[PDB]
Length: 258
Length: 256
Ligand code: NA
Ligand code: NA
Image (tube, rainbow over all chains, first blue to last red; front, side, top):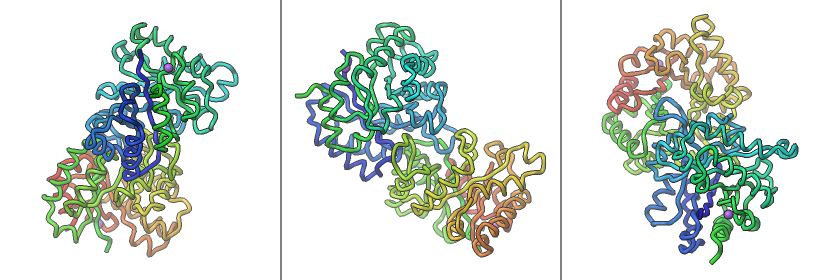
């Protein structure tokens, strides 16, 4: 009974004028009947969010939107950082936290991701909590255990009510940017284990409601068998999200077609 | 002479509505005649820049604006980062690089700051390159050498033409948000040392034109003595930049 979710992570691409054009094209390419069957959200750079807000609200589009990161702090002397309250006032629904690129390039560990998750929740945003193992962990066959500890650390101490407001994204690092998408059974194995660990972290009933996404080289050609898996509820899309035609097509596939 | 520069670093404060309100108030409070004697820029959070751009351009205000950070990378798979071309398209004039809060909380070293400086220059932005020593360095009397070392690292290998396009902000860490402003003579000591080092990294003529700011608990009461020093060309303002009247007053003081 979990509604599919497609989240388009633009990463560091597109100025505010290109952002408007991309969202216009996506909205025109994806017929409105599909939003009854799938949630579709675009996640632009911070500097683009205002422009996307005025478009989506002005035109009454059914796309939602979100941000690529958030500060763990409330307002204060944190030069360069963006607060949950700023994102909430812009009408963001989602915020990605702990993406692999930020865990590695900006030294975000599990405790930092937890603090960002809390800041998202305090401001009414839905955090997309990212986890995923490296090729070496995978090649050693210890990927399930690796992702479980990441999940435990990144949600540590949250109540059942709080966990019920998060989304989890499994993005194996070896699948980010590489054209090497996980097979459906690979995604299913880790996403099934994620939900099973959500049982202990916050009751079985909320475990069955939390949406778990696969991310990593997702496109219109591979999204179908991946999202079709019983424990995969959607996709965190990277490079495909910058291509209006492909992003709309893969979103419609995730919905189950017409 | 070098034209004074006042830069209001809002830090992580104000949503886009509050941003519109603050910029409107500053512009009303600082008469246009002052802009011939001082450059005044506001530096809002990324999410406020579109609203600030459209207001300043739309209502033809004389303030400029900038951002609080920029990526070293041109574009691509850097979730959460903002590129120099994104900022240039929004009409930003300045970008703060290497603020103490980012050097400490976000592990930005001299090499990262240099790369962000190059990305700023690549996109026609004016980087405000921040340097400054901690309390312990200062108490040992090692402050001048520490800041010169930081400066040489943050500009390593830049041409003289490229250095002429940067601004330097000396912000001792012990003065940031603490109310422990540097004395005028202490600010002059380091800012003069910075300009002296710029003569080596670039040239005498370039060093004579580069604007060197002081920051760290600046407000209307202490700005005058500090910016009146010969090698101090303005201020990088923290909390007072959020108070339109105070920010306008310290700007008018800086203009003479
Ligand atoms: Na599914
Ligand atoms: Na001066």
